[PDB]
């Protein structure tokens, strides 16, 4: 009942913000630009500093015209409407949002420890306890998101940032969506796609549990289970229902992964009658104190090395490009609700 009542309150609080979203809570000239932390085909993330408070933030900047051309309008509206409404210990917080003639802006907390991906590739693979610590945080995060009827749809090591306490904070809600029932969009990264996405089915929150299987495998092995050189080869392996496990995997880990990486979505852990509890009660998680993880009372496997809230050393280097704001409003109609 304690969990039920927690989730009931979580949904109440989400819905109030979902139904009345915040808008236009800062502007660009309140910030100084420091460094580009990441780039893509329609946006980028920049470390910025608020000129009055001195706080650092990660500012996600989306080019409206490019969002339209790449057919990401609904996805970007989803991302902002969801982020301004959620609240959970393992989600990067949205602090401000606004738009101008050219761009959409989401000003996020800055997590200086960098992406799990970097740390995983540095060390090779995580031990099972280390992978389990991160996996538990994803399980709780998905329990939270799914209870709000949200599907995340972009789990991968690059989207898991490591904070100053060594805990995960999930970033990038660009594919997140509120879904009662099924949804159909092809999105995600190839190695993490569930079979039902590849096969163009109407799919549901079970795709997130599949992706958790992929993530746990990759953390514990150092490479993902369906690895191949070309996407088509990855997709063939994903749909085949065959996975090979390293001999160093424990039997408990292999058993959990067979049930998360279940091609038949109606048999996949997280999507059965007992929901998330089939995962939380699995023997691989027997040492996990779920409440202590939620309360951040467990000592983390490692604390990322960084010098302060302005340190960018754990992120990589990109060409520094202008943030140009047109003299004329672009795509105003499409982004009215942002
Ligand atoms: O919130 C942050 O601290 C942050 C978010 C996103 C990114 C990245 F560029 F990789 F997408 C970096 C940092």
Image: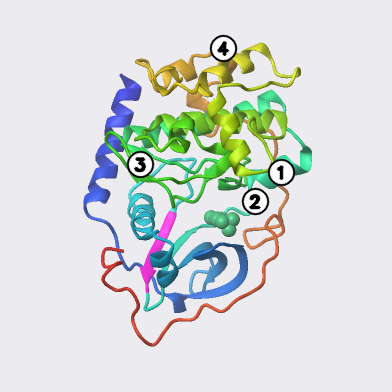
The residues tagged by marks 2 and 4 sit, at their Cα atoms, a distance apart of: 31 Å
- Along the viewing direction, whichever of 86 and 70 lies nearer the viewer: 70
Q: Which residues are magenta?
A: 94-99
N-term mark: 1 or 4: 1
Classify the position of the N terminus by image quarter.
top left
The residue that mark 1 highlights is: 119
Kindly tell me whether mark 2's CB lies below 8 Å from ligand 1: yes
Residue in the picture at 57% in, 74% down? 33
- Ligand 1 is found in the corner quadrant, namely bottom right
The residues tagged by marks 1 and 4 sit, at their Cα atoms, a distance apart of: 27 Å
Residue in the picture at 66% in, 44% down? 117
Kindly tell me whether mark 1's CB lies below 8 Å from ligand 1: no
Residue in the picture at 52% in, 77% down? 323
N-term mark: 1 or 3: 1
**Considering the numbered disc 3 on the image, is that residue within a helix, a strand or a loop?**
loop
- Asked whether the beta carbons under mark 2 and mark 1 sit within 8 Å of each other, the answer is yes
Labelled disc at residue 283? 4
The residues tagged by marks 3 and 4 sit, at their Cα atoms, a distance apart of: 34 Å
Labelled disc at residue 114? 2
**Considering the numbered disc 4 on the image, is that residue within a helix, a strand or a loop?**
helix
Whether residue 214 sits left or right of residue 197 in the image: it is right
Disc 2 crowd rating (10 Å Cα; few below 14, some 14-19, many 20+) is: many
Labelled disc at residue 184? 3
Labelled disc at residue 2? none
Disc 4 crowd rating (10 Å Cα; few below 14, some 14-19, many 20+) is: some
Disc 1 crowd rating (10 Å Cα; few below 14, some 14-19, many 20+) is: some
Whether residue 116 sits left or right of residue 271 in the image: it is right
The residues tagged by marks 2 and 1 sit, at their Cα atoms, a distance apart of: 8 Å
**Considering the numbered disc 1 on the image, is that residue within a helix, a strand or a loop?**
helix
The residues tagged by marks 1 and 3 sit, at their Cα atoms, a distance apart of: 33 Å
Please identify the dominant SS of the magenta region: strand
């Amino acid at each position: 009942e304690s969990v039920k009542e927690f989730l009931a309150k979580a949904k109440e609080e989400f819905l109030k913000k979902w139904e009345s979203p915040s808008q236009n809570t800062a502007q660009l000239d309140h910030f100084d630009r420091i460094k580009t932390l990441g780039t893509g085909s329609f946006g980028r993330v920049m470390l910025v500093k608020h000129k009055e408070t001195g706080n650092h933030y990660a500012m996600k900047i989306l080019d409206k015209q490019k969002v339209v051309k790449l057919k990401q309008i609904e996805h970007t509206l989803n991302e902002k409407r969801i982020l301004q409404a959620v609240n959970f210990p393992f989600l990067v917080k949205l602090e401000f949002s606004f738009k101008d003639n050219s761009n959409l802006y989401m000003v996020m907390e800055y997590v200086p420890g960098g992406e799990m991906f970097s740390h995983l590739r540095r060390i090779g693979r995580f031990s099972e306890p280390h992978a389990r610590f991160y996996a538990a945080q994803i399980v709780l995060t998905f329990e939270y998101l799914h209870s709000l009827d949200l599907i995340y749809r972009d789990l991968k090591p690059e989207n898991l940032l490591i904070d100053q306490q060594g805990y995960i904070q999930v970033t990038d809600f660009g594919f997140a969506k509120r879904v009662k029932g099924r949804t159909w969009t092809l999105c995600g990264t190839p190695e993490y796609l569930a079979p039902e996405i590849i096969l163009s089915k109407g799919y549901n929150k079970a795709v997130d549990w599949w992706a958790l299987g992929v993530l746990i495998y990759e953390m514990a092995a150092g490479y993902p289970p369906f690895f191949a050189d070309q996407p088509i080869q990855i997709y063939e392996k994903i749909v085949s229902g065959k996975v090979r496990f390293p001999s160093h995997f424990s039997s408990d880990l292999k058993d959990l992964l067979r049930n998360l990486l279940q091609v038949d979505l109606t048999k996949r852990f997280g999507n059965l009658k007992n929901g998330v509890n089939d995962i939380k009660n699995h023997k691989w998680f027997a040492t996990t104190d779920w409440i202590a993880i939620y309360q951040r009372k467990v000592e983390a496997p490692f604390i990322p090395k960084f010098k302060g809230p302005g340190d960018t050393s754990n992120f990589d280097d990109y060409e520094e490009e202008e943030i140009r704001v047109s003299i004329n409003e672009k795509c105003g109609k499409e982004f009215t609700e942002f």
